[PDB]
Amino acid sequence: LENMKKEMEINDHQLSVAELEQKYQTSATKGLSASLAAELLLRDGPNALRPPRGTPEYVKFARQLAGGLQCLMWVAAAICLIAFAIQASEGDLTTDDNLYLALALIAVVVVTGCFGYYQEFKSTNIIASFKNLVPQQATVIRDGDKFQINADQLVVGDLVEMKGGDRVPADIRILQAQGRKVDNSSLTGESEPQTRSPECTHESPLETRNIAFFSTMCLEGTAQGLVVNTGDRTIIGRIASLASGVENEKTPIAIEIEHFVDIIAGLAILFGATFFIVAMCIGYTFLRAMVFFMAIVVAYVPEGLLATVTVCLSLTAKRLASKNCVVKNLEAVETLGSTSVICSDKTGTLTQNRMTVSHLWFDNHIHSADTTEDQSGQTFDQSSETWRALCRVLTLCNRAAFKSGQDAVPVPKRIVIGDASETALLKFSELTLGNAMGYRERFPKVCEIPFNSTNKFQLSIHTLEDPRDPRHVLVMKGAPERVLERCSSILIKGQELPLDEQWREAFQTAYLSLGGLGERVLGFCQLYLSEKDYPPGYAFDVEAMNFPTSGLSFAGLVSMIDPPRATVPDAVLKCRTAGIRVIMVTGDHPITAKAIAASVGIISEGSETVEDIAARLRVPVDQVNRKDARACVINGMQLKDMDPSELVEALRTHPEMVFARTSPQQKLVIVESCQRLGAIVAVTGDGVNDSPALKKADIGVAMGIAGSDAAKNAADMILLDDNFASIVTGVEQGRLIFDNLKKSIAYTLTKNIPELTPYLIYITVSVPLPLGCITILFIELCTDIFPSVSLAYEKAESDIMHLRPRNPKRDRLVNEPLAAYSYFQIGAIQSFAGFTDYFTAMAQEGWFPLLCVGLRPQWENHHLQDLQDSYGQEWTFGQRLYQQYTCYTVFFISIEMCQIADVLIRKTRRLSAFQQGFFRNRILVIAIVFQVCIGCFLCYCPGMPNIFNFMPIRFQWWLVPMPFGLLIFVYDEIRKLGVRCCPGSWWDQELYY
Amino acid sequence: RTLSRWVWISLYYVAFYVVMSGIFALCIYVLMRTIDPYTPDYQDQLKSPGVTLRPDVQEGSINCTSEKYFFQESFLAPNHTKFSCKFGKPCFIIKMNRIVKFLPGNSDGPPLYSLHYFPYYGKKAQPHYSNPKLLNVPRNRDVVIVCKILAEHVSFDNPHDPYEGKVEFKLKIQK
């Protein structure tokens, strides 16, 4: 399947022209026969790519319904519904109870469902991004005569002709070309035009001049070439197939949740069967033991949980959007908090993807211009007389012009018409000099000899602006060696000086050096033409050297470089502090890639690749211990050859890696290599060449503006801003929530125990049911909701960036220490709080607790209007029921009172309420007040007696759980203190989340 | 799952649940202190008396007549047991649900309490304290009947405790 696509291509550029036909069954001059073109059409198929096999029906809604969690709620709803159906066996109360519960469950799955399904309904789309560019016709030669045919018709063997402007229809072997240039950015990510000639330039097929690739567009010139490959078979076609057809998989948060549901179920079963068996030994048939087991579901399963996690995830995502960080998926909020390594594309990601100027040599000194977009750097030199003279030639001996109508946009940002080197000079001068146009105007261009291929140099003759001369000035530029050949003198400072052999090499030095920077160099000189020889009028001949070309005054040298985005070197540093490995992966050449690597902080001071050391040592490389090199830079042509085990070692071996000149399949390979290690890898990229890797990465991040549609589709996240620094914020939004979520789990779970125990005691003790099904739903659906959600607001107890990424396998979101804490300790304190209120209401009523035992049959007995309390009085069915209902209400309230404590304690794992300040979280405090207020409402509001069987509570009743609440706050607070004091041992080991 | 260290668990809970079954019981035995032996803190629940019946759906003592309320004194132990007054076509018997210190107030179909007893003193105060027919023409059919009690003190809750101050039963007598 996909695996073959990962391998690099193998070709036929070495083959002779004649040989290629022989293989093809084609005629070079004439082209395939019509008959023969058809055949081959059927044999092979169309010259069309296999439509994006990506279409997940709107039926996908149904995917949010199931999950693992929603299941737990489904099975639970289904168990309720069964129970009901079993309660069909007689005339039952469940019309309010069991059917109501099972419907509530289903409804929480559905709602939660919907909600999820929306926050996600915003994304996807990839094939349609690719299709956004989708051939039309081709001109082919068949039977000696050319015609334009539907592009699908093209087959291997035929003759195709392409000119400047057209898109290469298929993979082609160039047989004939005049002055043709192509754009191969689809392959390389690099736009500058590449020659196409008939002779094979290199071994690599991607490199050779003789091949023109589909998904590429002939920039200029004209060519012809034989179709080697069609449709899926072309180099890019393979890339296409090798993309959308990807299985998205599970997120870590999603995994953590799944892993939660297992534990929870784990308990809900264990207990639920245990209560089948314990009820058996008591006096309960298969009729009754069974109804309990299923009964044991709701108490066990937090109905409110799914909702809370989502609103928590949604709430956090909102903060990030505020951040100019859009998140397509809710699950995406967390993932960032577990990125070990980042594989970053260089151009347009790390860098602005915007050529510029470099340095300068003059005054026998090397100068360094500011390359930055914002031009944050400083001013190298205004002073020098030489500098101006040099500026003059740069502005004057220059064709380029800025496009009209962006005086709005900044100089380095505006589009210029002209070659890159000439634009670089214009921008340079326009920035430090003032308007270029100015200078042009002021020194009108008489005549000039455009940059020839043979001359390797471009000159101009201008009337001098200085009104006292307006004599003629000669300015030229071109290959540095050529400009020197052409000079007698050198403008050092203001004044000319003989060009001795000493300067000849000081120049030769600079030229070498700048040229080592991986910069392109140009030489500059000018000549104040003798006015005797040239009259004001004087006519210049561009055709034949009227005027002097040799013995000119050599002004200076102009180099260039490349830069990144402002934020990026930092953002990189932050990530590294984060203990994240950053790995460059770029299509670009190695000299450039390494330079940027240094610039950004991918490669740190001191680091060294074998070859650097190599070179400082003065020693051959074989000689150099590999292990001495922390850093590595590997060309794609070398990476091709290597095994994936060899890749794994390189990866194991080096802290700072740069893969340069990599193909899209190689980027993919690196990532996979990364993942094999078992690290979580963010790929950040801008280009179509980044697609398979972005699509591979645990999280693909794409640039919003620069980014090609392809990258955007392929990605999980879009940096709308192209603000790399965002990536840092994104990683800091994947750790504060993960923890805050456990707090909300512990909070929600703790109340489960106060809900469970009353039903159990009810069976074991044979006492009147202390809490009802309805009462439970008010806690889970009403009261616990705000407080649970509110936990998301919680802050860091420590500097979170400082700790290492979580080992996904070892540190789970919900762990046994949470259960023990929620269930074993805190929940248990909660339950007694509830039970107490129970006893107080009945006792006050005339039913002392000792009398309570064994009573439920009489109490429940509908027939007995007679039930005698301890005092000796007699209560009807309804009467004592009202009291019981009051109990259900008070128990409900007792939990909310104990939930206040739980809320407080839950706010911090390590820290003391005092340190944190339970106080700052406004959302949480709001939870206590609204929570209470909901309870009071349920109690006080009239009609709530019938609708939810909630009865009014005396003021006294409110207090019962108070000592319980307070003990919880103390008991936890103590414990944490203990945990701070000895980090090493026991409390932390058992209890620490 | 530890090695060795279960002590530091097993001994833990021992004197921590211990501490917690010990505070809880702590809080109960305190509550219990602040209640009368003879009278509950709230009477409100029982507020209107309900009516219940025998059916299923002395001497010592004092001789008495049909009069006003007999006050025994306060509800205190300083006196010994307060003295209580003496007392086909089925026979159903109705009583009024005992409520301490409550003085009831008084000073077609198909075919079909003396004040001297109150106030009831309550069990602890009075142990053997006794609280105070369908001759019908039809036979061999279910008959729905409702018996109720009257007073200014008495109230009925038709929507709720159908018991409250009233009965509802279906008699049948198959001869």
Image (spheres, coloured by chain):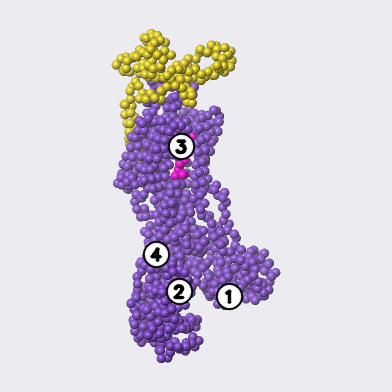
Chain colours: A purple, B yellow
> Which residue carries the number 1 mark?
A222
**Three-letter residue code for mark 4:** Ala
The image's mark for residue A566 is 4
Question: Which residue sits at x=34%, y=82%?
Answer: A494
Q: Nearer the viewer, residue A313 or A911?
A: A313
Q: CA distance from mark 3 to mark 1?
A: 76 Å
CB atoms of marks 4 and 3 within 8 Å:
no
Question: Which residue sits at x=49%, y=58%?
Answer: A715
Q: Nearer the viewer, residue A732 or B168?
A: B168
Find the magenta span and give its range: A294-308
Residue A144 in percent (x, y) is at 67, 75
Q: Nearer the viewer, residue A273 or A923?
A: A923
Marks 4, 1 in one chain: yes
> Which residue carries the number 3 mark?
A777
Q: CA distance from mark 2 to mark 1?
A: 26 Å
Locate the N terminus of chain A by quadrant.
bottom right
Marks 4, 3 in one chain: yes
Mark before the other along the chain sequence, 4 or 3: 4
The reply to whether residue A76 is in sight is: no
> Which residue carries the number 2 mark?
A423
CB atoms of marks 3 and 2 within 8 Å:
no
Mark before the other along the chain sequence, 4 or 1: 1
For disc 3, the neighbor class at 10 Å (few under 14, some 14 to 19, many from 20) is many
Marks 2, 4 in one chain: yes
> Which chain's residue wears label 2?
A
Within the magenta stretch, is there residue A298?
yes
Q: CA distance from mark 4 to mark 3?
A: 54 Å
For disc 1, the neighbor class at 10 Å (few under 14, some 14 to 19, many from 20) is some
Q: CA distance from mark 3 to mark 2?
A: 71 Å
**Three-letter residue code for mark 3:** Leu
Within the magenta stretch, is there residue A800?
no
Q: Which is more foreground, mark 3 or mark 2?
A: 2
